[PDB]
Every structure is written in C-alpha cells, then in structure tokens.
C-alpha cells in the first residue's frame, strides 16, 4: 500500500489567497505568474516534474517529494496593512525546509524578487539554469517596471481563457505594446490571444486579413526566434485553418521549447482534429497534470473548439467525479 | 483519496523471468540491459520520468500513466523450446496497448532488436531521439556482435555491485577489450569497475599507480568526450582520494550527460563525504526511484564506502519497513 515519494516531483501550492478575507488583485496575479514561470522553467529545463496546483482547490495523495508553498502573511501591526509573500520549499521525505523567503512586493521590484527566488531555487535544488532559459527570460518579461502589474494581469486573464477574459487580456497587451514598442514578445502574445478570440467570435474578412498579416510579420521577427510563442501562434493559426499537419509540426516544436499546460492542450486539439482521440486524451491529461484545475479544464473543454470531456477524455471525466 | 495518473511517468516491469521455471542467463541479462537503456535514455533525453522496476519484486500504488512490460513467452510447441520476448507498452489511463512486439533473440541480433524497439517507442511516445542520444548509443554498445552477450552479462554484474560480481565484470570487460581494441567505452567501463574494486580490496602501490595511469589515459581520449562514463571515473577516483569538490564537480557533469540510478548514488556518496546527509538521502532516494530494488540498495549501502540506511536515509528505511 506504500506510495514511494519522488524527490524530483514537485507541487506548487498557494495558501491564504484572501490576505484581507477578500481578493484582491495585484499581489495575487503576480504570485500566480511567478508560480507558472517556476513550474514551466523547471519542466522545460530540468529533470524535475512540476505540478502547478495554484489553481487547484483539492488536496489528494501524491508522490511529490517536494512542495513549494506561496502564502500571504499579515504582520497585523495595523488594520488593512498589506500582506507580505512567504515562499517556502519543503522536502516531504523528512519535512525539512529547503528554502524560506519573505518577500515585500513594491509595484516595481517584481522582476528583482522573482530573480532572487530563481537564484535561490537553483541553489536549493542543485539546478543550474541553462543558457536558453536565461535568454528566454530576458525576452518574455517586460523590462519597463511600470508595466509589470498589467502584464501579470493579462497573463492571469489568458489562463482563464473565456471570451471576456481574453478580450481584457488583448486590451491590456495592446496598452503594453503602445507603451513598450521594443517588448516584441507582448506583440506576439497579443496575436496569440487575438487568434484565439477570433475562434471565439470570428472576425470579418478585412479584420481577419489584418490579423493574418500581423501574424506573418511577427513569426519572421528574428528576436522571437527560439521562443515557443511563435510556434503557438503557428499552431493555433493552422488549427483555425484546419491545417492538421502544419499545426502538428508547429506544436511539437513549441513543446520542445516550452513544456507547458497550454502547449499540451493545443497538442490535444491537433490530435482531435486528426481523429486521434486517445492521443488527444493523453495530451489533455498531461496538461491537467501540469496545471490541474478549472483554468486548464476550461481550455480543454472550450479552447479553439468544444471538446467533450466525457467522450474524448473519459479517464479525466471519471477522475473528476471520483 | 483519488491519485492522478501522470501520462509522462512510465514504469518498466519484467514478467516470467523463469521461462523454464529456472534462470536462465542470456536472454535475461539482455532484457535487463534493454530495460536499463530505455529507462536511462528517456530519463536523460525526454521529459518522461521512468522507473525501471525490473529488479523490484513488489507491486505498489503508483501514479505511472504507462507501463512497459517485458515478458518471456513460451510457444509450447515442444519441450525445452526457447521463449520469445514479448514487449508491450500499456496506457494505464484507459488500458489500451500502445506497442506490442514479439522478439526472437538470436545471439547476434540483440542490437537490431533493440533498435527496432527504440524506433517503435519513439513513434508510440511522440518522442524523437536527439542527436546526442543517437551519438551516445553508437559509442556505448559493442558493434562486434559476438561480444554482446558477454557485454550484457558484465552490465548485470555491475548492477549487482558486490565484490565477486565486480571481479567477474572486470574479467568479462578485459576479454572484450582484448577482442575489440576499438571499443574504447569497454576500456572506460573496466576502469570504472576497477576503481570501485580497489575501494573493495585496495591495490598495492604499484598496481594503484598502474590503475591511475590507465585512468589518466582514458579520460583524455577525445572519442569519450561527452560521455557520462568519463565523469563517473573522475567522480569515483576523486571520492577514493577524498577530494570532495573535484568529485562534486565531476558527478554533476556526469548527471547532465546521463540521468541514471548510479550517478545519483555517486552524488549521494559525495554529499555524505561533504557532511551533508539530507542532500545525500535525497540523492539516494532519487536513485531508488530510478531503479528500485536490491541492486540499487546494495550500491547505496555499500558502494565506495558503507552507508547506514537507518541513519543517513531514514525515509527509505521506514519505506522499506512499511
């Protein structure tokens, strides 16, 4: 009956989301973005397997050898005092604390704090960060500090995936693009969001041609070479056009560049389009493993086209019911 | 209470080791070597996590989404007819068979069969093999077919790890080296075995100087560049000399090149030498995850120097008792 702990399997949890009994946007979408970045970085660039459980409200038995916990903590020195962020890495094999950070976030220092956490995690996990990871991080985060809060907000809206959330993400990204023309990645993320929005509410012919021209210009930009986002755009554009082989090629390259819940959802959608439901279900279960919860389920059920969890993904249907 | 299956966690099992109710060397050490190669290849070169349970006699609950089963099957067309090897990959999420092979092994075709299995696994798992993996496989296996059976036998003796087994491995490798001077890897594996044998039964001054000269010549050979074995030799040689920093540097490079149970045992031994028992226990638990059973436990408890599982690795002590 014994379940063996795996020291290279890590869960990320969030505790006390309601610092002031209420939420609470700002520190929270930042923390959600940090959690996603840590999970994606380790999944892509190390032999750790990370389950981002930030969006997962259930506690179940798991073989995770380590747990990274993000908690908001109030010093209670006066009413309505801002919480600080506590981040702890615990080894579940013996209960020891490997990393214990207290972070005060200041609407400006988000990248510096994140960098400190990444440096400390590298030391605690005996895990140097490879060159491609360091280069990628330089390209996928805004360096104008004033824009960070809204960038993290757009990210959280993307995770939610519904039409209203994507509409707001596109708006936020459009503002960032205007404010920071050099931050090419934001232009690419906005095109990805916009193609998905087109699948939700189809553009007229003129607007579609404009979006397609924008995609064409983006995917050839040399500074976005070697980023998963270009391949996500190529994959979603091909899915929309029903070009199955082109989408399959794109998303597998995207996955090499970024092991993320979203890339596995997109691979699932390609497999469904190919008439391969078992392979689709396997990709969707992978996505759910990487980031379990309502956000990933929303994308599985609704992203690009509708997918029946009972029919296409019966293991997950049964799991969710159990 | 639900445990979520992870589609990127794979166990490898062996069924019907006693083809003729008795063992049974030949097909068995080949199958053990194939299992180890598959696990190490996927662990090193993909985002799959593989648990090689070939040496593990217990069935426990696990989150493994897929199981690769090696089984010996007798056609029973006449008494004492040789078994063939059945290899099946099963998806535990739905019970579907992903790969189903029937292999007749002929004292010659071991590499060809293994290549077929690796090609088929690449297709079944949507997992292309990277260039470094293809190059490595060309260097770590003998290409003189007549030597394969004994090479796999030496490998199994290495896994066992006790003094008599290593003595026999060294002998077998010495014969291979004489028969195949070009197969430089065998010379490196023999030096690794021989340094470990020296930790078991120390060589006199003259013989130690000869071994150290041999190590010096081996580690500079350009064709063994980019192979974990050179770093394993460097790490074990430094451990024997009590050079902790040199050993730590070597084994971490070795791990980058090969995610294997043996490299994590060696990292554990370095951490113990550094006075870092918690980090050692974590490395040892990693090794046990990669290849659970008596062989890995033997190396944890006895490799290079003696290690108390109750004191140094209490989680594993308790697990084994539970």
Image (spheres, coloured by chain):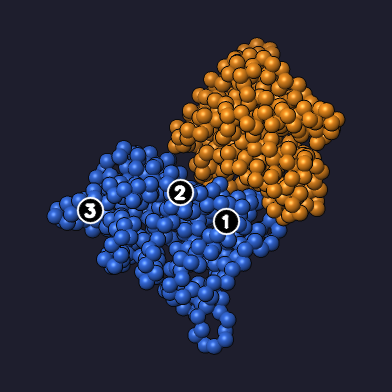
Chain colours: A blue, B orange
Q: Mark 2, mark 3: which one is toward the viewer?
A: 2
Residue A25 located left or right of residue A197: right
A208 lies above or below A245: below
Residue A284 shown left or right of residue A51 in the figure = left
Q: Which mark is residue A122?
A: 1
Q: Earlier in the sequence, mark 3 or mark 1?
A: 1
Question: Dot 3 lies on which element?
Answer: helix
Give percent across and percent down for residue A111. 46, 65
Mark 3 and mark 1, same subunit? yes
Question: Residue A301, percent across and down?
Answer: 37, 54
Q: CA distance from mark 2 to mark 3?
A: 26 Å
**What residue is at 17 percent from the left and 52 percent from the top?**
A209
Mark 3 nearby-residue class (10 Å; few <14, some 14–19, many ≥20): some
Q: Secondary structure at mark 1?
A: helix
> Can marks 2 and 3 be said to lie on one chain?
yes
Distance (Cα) linking label 2 and label 1 = 15 Å
Residue A208 visible to the viewer? no
Callout 2: chain: A
What residue is drawn where x is 21% and y is 50%?
A212
Badge 1: few (under 14), some or many (20 or more) residues near its Cα, within 10 Å? some
Residue B80 x, y percent position in the rendering: 69, 13
Closer to the camera, A220 or B265?
Answer: A220
Circle 2 sits on which residue? A132
Nearer-N-terminus badge (2/3): 2
In front of the other: A278 or B199: B199
Confirm whether circles 2 and 1 share one chain: yes
**Tag 1, which chain?**
A
Is A34 drawn above or below residue B206 in the view shown?
Answer: below
């Amino acid at each position: 009956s014994r379940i063996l702990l795996n020291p290279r399997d890590i869960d990320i949890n969030m505790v006390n989301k309601s610092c002031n009994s209420w939420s609470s946007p700002y520190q929270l979408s930042y923390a959600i973005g940090v959690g996603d970045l840590v999970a994606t970085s380790l999944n892509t660039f190390s032999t750790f397997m990370v389950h981002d459980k930030i969006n997962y409200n259930i506690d179940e038995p798991s073989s995770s050898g380590k747990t990274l916990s993000i908690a908001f903590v109030n010093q209670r020195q006066y009413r309505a005092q801002q919480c600080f962020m506590s981040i702890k890495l615990v080894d579940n094999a013996d209960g020891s604390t490997m990393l214990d950070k207290r972070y005060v976030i200041t609407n400006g220092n988000q990248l510096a704090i994140q960098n400190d956490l990444l440096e400390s995690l590298s030391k605690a996990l005996n895990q140097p960060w490879p060159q491609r990871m360091q280069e990628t991080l330089q390209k996928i985060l805004p360096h104008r500090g004033a824009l960070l809060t809204n960038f993290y907000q757009a990210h959280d809206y993307l995770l939610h995936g519904d039409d209203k959330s994507l509409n707001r993400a596109s708006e936020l990204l459009g503002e960032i693009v205007q404010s920071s023309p050099e931050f090419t990645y934001a232009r690419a993320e906005k095109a990805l969001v916009d193609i998905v929005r087109h699948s939700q509410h189809p553009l007229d012919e003129k607007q579609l041609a404009a979006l397609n021209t924008e995609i064409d210009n983006i995917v050839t930009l040399p500074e976005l070479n070697n980023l998963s986002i270009i391949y996500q755009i190529k994959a979603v554009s091909a899915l929309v056009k029903g070009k199955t082989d082109e989408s399959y090629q794109a998303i597998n390259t995207g996955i090499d560049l970024e092991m993320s819940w979203l890339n596995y959802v997109l691979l699932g959608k390609v497999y469904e389009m190919k008439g391969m439901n078992r392979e689709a279900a396997d990709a969707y279960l992978t996505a759910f493993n990487l980031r379990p919860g309502a956000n990933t389920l929303y994308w599985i059920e609704n992203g690009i086209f509708q997918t029946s969890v009972p029919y296409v993904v019966p293991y997950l249907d049964k799991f969710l019911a159990s």
